[PDB]
Image (cartoon, rainbow over all chains, first blue to last red; front, top):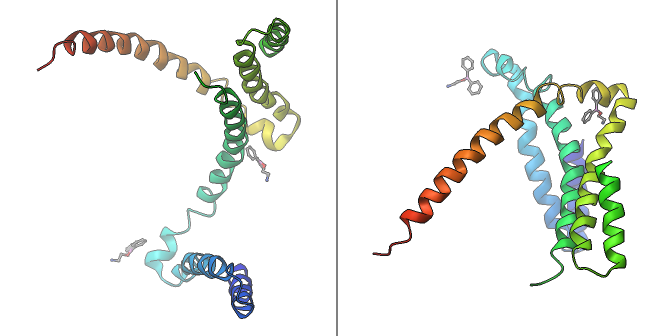
Length: 87
Length: 87
Ligand SMILES: NCCOB(c1ccccc1)c1ccccc1
Ligand SMILES: NCCOB(c1ccccc1)c1ccccc1
């Protein structure tokens, strides 16, 4: 659905000649290629292999990102404030 | 306690206009953000996940650091003495 919405939006933006049509077109291209895993389930070779990604792999990747991004922000604000003074 | 002590010290230093108040203020900001894990225990979602850090994760990270830092010093002194002579 997202790939379809962005593609429709990108083509709508291209009609209005706004420069932001290209980023949406490129994001649609990235999402569309990633959507090709949906058709791996049609073959026993690729279907069984791609089972153990959504169950465990994809879930725990989100867990690290949320915790890490919070303290990435905490250190980023710390470094900028401390580095504002020159020698 | 450390975050409170450094924050009090940093504000005390700021009254005396010493430049070292900023590093203590920034260290307090880093520690204060890290103290936010204490409130993860209030939710079942985050409480159970954050259990397996203090028991095993944090302890063994200290083990590597103490052993590695000793021989980091040993190689550092070795490299400087050996690199003192130019070609
Ligand atoms: N040369 C075709 C190999 O096919 B795959 C495959 C073949 C037999 C059994 C299981 C998998 C495959 C390749 C990449 C990713 C996932 C599966
Ligand atoms: N979108 C909320 C996800 O919540 B977390 C979560 C949800 C259900 C079960 C276990 C944990 C979570 C996220 C990051 C780190 C730790 C836990």
